[PDB]
Length: 4
Length: 422
Ligand code: NA
Ligand SMILES: [Zn+2]
Image (cartoon, rainbow over all chains, first blue to last red):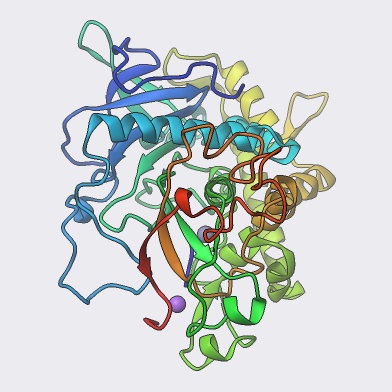
């Protein structure tokens, strides 16, 4: 997953 | 090639590698057409309204209720042509990954990473866990259970929310107890992210339009790395996080990033995880592998008739690189464990894949996405297994010109800008  | 067959979405089902299947989501669902592109790996060209019952609709909440970095389009991946291109795009990315030594190593580890047979409540018997299987409709209309390690499926409501999803157990934490579980990666090869070449701009939420495009092979590799941790049951609990103190924009908002993510990105990011916690995790998973060896030693019979107990014991011996002594007993060798653990957590990282693909990419996971672009990597005139967007012997070969959305603008359509919306 990516965050920002 | 990693994928021996160049599938067409409209190819007739055969009940073997082109078939209608159902997944163990504990709920009801109509069969979906799926494609087995490699041993233990399937692709379902459908939006994921299956793994989570609470996400069974592409309906987006309110109209300002969701995060800045999100993109909705309930119509995406609803037509045959889209599904055909989705299949070809995902296949192409697997080949791109497999064309590198690092990718070959990772994919090999994933295929060998069969979810442990820990479904038995009787220690003297080895049994599979049904949620690590899918039900395949055979030519006669009947269902047959098939174990698999990985499924690539389209995204749910938020098109750009790529992530690994897997079915849990009532008491076992399969992704963190050494067992592993079948991984469903929500992913799309039809979109990509825009980032900035300057670190101080890329890590600032108020600057940058997203001049460079992320190579989707890296994005998929990121998820495959997570999948690898989860398949070997060594994923770090998401509750273990880094209270970011290296970026004022993160700090002022108390943003916390999981160690699992920092580990997966690698490079300098992985250093934020201190030695103390790093050692704690290693020891913890070492013990989990010891339990697997102990469980294998107690098993004297196998449940089902799909494989022999001897074959399955060897399967896990190879997966976990266990030692088999004179007495035929299995044990975990510290050196072999550290070697495998390190391979899965330090060798397989986003940062290392960037080095292998020779592409421009975000320098840290602790940045701020700039935008999302619509792309099409299926045409060889747009993207290739070997060069991605940076096509050799063209103006796009040097300086990552192919990833430069301004130079290679015909390959990108900006759909949304995220800058300033954080
Ligand atoms: Na953010
Ligand atoms: Zn991630």
